[PDB]
Length: 270
Length: 272
Image (cartoon, rainbow over all chains, first blue to last red; front, side, top):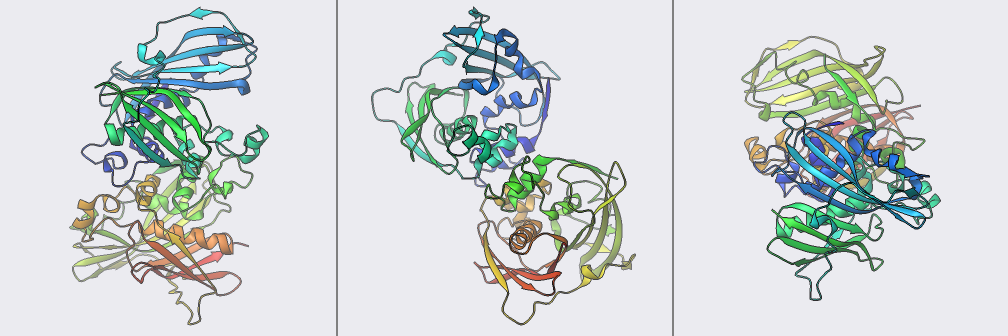
């Protein structure tokens, strides 16, 4: 499963996460510090054309409409990550945990440089699937950062920033690979008992990641739990605590409805 | 002859850069029943290949690519509606050349066909104005009347007007459609080309104008315009339009912030 990407993918993605023309490092391929926002590494999901669904063989009675992306963990192993090239992704289940009539699956991936074999990204996605059966198995150990609950300490946030979400952001963001109609088609969305189309959880995650970098600098590890929906046109509020020399704990709040979109989350600074 | 392979992603990215939003899913969602492309999309072969820029620098002397300015553009869509995906093959043929002092005015033509059928999709006539250059004085082919029509704005007040904000970040998005010229994003190159800061692509202004016109008047299959003034990211456009027959909408594009004219001598031909 090979994915060839270039500066156009990088810039399209960076802009979707709020990169501006003031930040030429994000939007301009000839800038001396031209760079990709590291959450870009998850996009192998949409460019590893069939292989991505390899966890399904371990499931029974699997209905895709009943699947939820509950957690995501990403690591960058080669700093800084590349802004162009060719990467090969290997997918492997990490764990399956039967829970009543449902299953929690942890699905792992590793993306390497296709012309040297150098490890670039790794991802661990946690999926929650209703009305599904599976074996109770553990295929691999997980990094501490991936399973850390990252509870916000009982003090004031060291940082707070508001991030308006364009009413049209999902329309742009989906060009990075995820075409799910839930994020764009009102008929589909309302048909699915949503008030209107929702923003991609990974876009919320990225937006959060970008905002945190503007303040705290770059990170090579990120983990978060998805706890609530976000609508385009709404405003996100990122609350952040500096919890070690290494580690920024955060939450992403939705101002307009007084909910929480991202919780149990942190980044590890380079 | 360069082969251009494009898909829904290119179309939506282009359409969004021209101000298309989720209020108009026909421009921004590929599974919309009316999914379509704003037809200026057909010009992109002008900037998105190497044989599109080296194929005319062929009668050029002392050419600097950074000293290039786009002066007029004509586009015709021959196959309606324009495809939202496919493979297109383009042939470039010189139309005319002229020295004007130490600079050079060049009219360069192109025809774009489907790569699977040989069917004519788009025709383009670009007019370039290049600073600090030198060339022969020549004329190689005839031109459609619509391309050389001066389309003088009628003396009456416009039949229609609308303002179009230009995001400070729009050139960064627009250039992803193919024209990477650093003049539109890098202050160093913009000043190298004698502008105070990066300028918006002439073709983005052109396309923003086209999009506003379509919203009011419907689809067109033929467009021509003269570029007469710079536009900076962050400024506000004003499209002025005059209905000049059941067929033809004459327009100008003004810059509200500085009281200048960015596009003049311009019109579209409405589809049937």
